[PDB]
Each structure stands twice: as C-alpha cells, then as structure tokens.
Length: 58
Image (cartoon, helix red, strand yellow):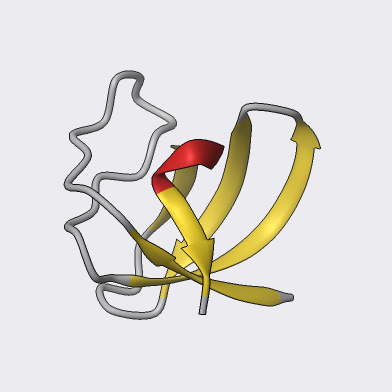
C-alpha cells in the first residue's frame, strides 16, 4: 500500500517477523499494531512483522 526503505539490517525476533537488510524496499501492508508493522519485502518477496522505526518512506 505504501513503500518504505529499510534503514538497518534486522534479524527476526519472532517466528512471524520479517528478516531484512538495510536498503530493502518494503511494502507496508498493515500498521495497526503501532511500533510493529506488517511488511512485504519487494527485494526478497518475504512477508512479516518489522519494527516501524526501521523504515523510512521512499
């Protein structure tokens, strides 16, 4: 729905988290959980939760 870029590498901290590298383009699919957003990585094709402060708008 909106595209962001990852600011830092992130290793998943739950089984439902997305792992991603700095610079990945991430589509934000849901943001209702505040500091944790559901994202889809356009760079890798994977999906999961991310920390909202790890991304900035493209």
